[PDB]
Image (cartoon, rainbow, N blue to C red; front, side, top):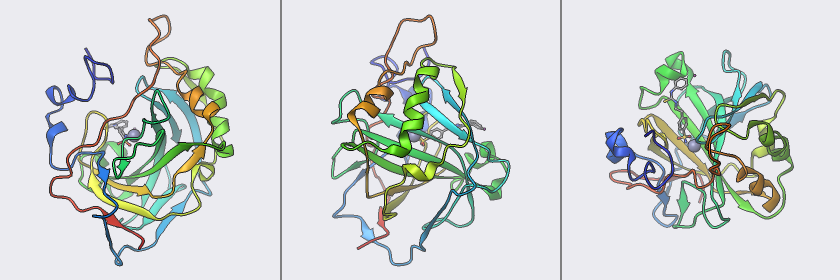
Length: 258
Ligand SMILES: NS(=O)(=O)c1ccc(CCNC(=S)Nc2ccc(I)cc2)cc1
Ligand SMILES: [Zn+2]
């Protein structure tokens, strides 16, 4: 009886195994655009992905991760609200059964069809497992997906998903350039929060871009053909793998822009 996204093991249950689920800095949150304050002190954001080394794509039973070589400073995030250097380790998405839901963050209670998380860890903690134990251990870059025009830079991901249909399957996934998943603008909101899946650790500086990327109906339909189950288990489509908005509590969402 492991955590997941069903009726019996979904987000409303997680607090029983992971009591931090009801903590003071949980994610995701609703971004109230009228309440978020421009912070002129935010340094410019630096996304340096030119040397990124992708290795593998993995269905982990909750989502699929595109994993990077993080054994040196290649692909890094710096600036914005961050002190120091954060190394890209993986990206993944959350998505819906229908185009009207799927994002974890919301904007004035609007849900997007999906949300991309580019996960980075603070190099001053030496490894990812040490970084998740620290309040400034991770920086997750969150990007909304809406359905419209295809995202050309996403199609290499869409085309390998047939090869990792079920939980525990992986495939080689070299030379993928995550710059092809970015919108034009790097304007963002930022707040202190958590991982959005168990173990729900309060270790994340969230950086959520205001400009969504557009993906096609056919691209998101291929995400929804993935399976939560393992091979030779009953088929359960990998859809609605999102946690809903959590209470903001004693936090302020800061805007990088006027
Ligand atoms: N949705 S999200 O963006 O907030 C998100 C991001 C990341 C995670 C991965 C948690 N893994 C952990 S805690 N330990 C771990 C430690 C070392 C290694 I190498 C692998 C695993 C979860 C959720
Ligand atoms: Zn995520």
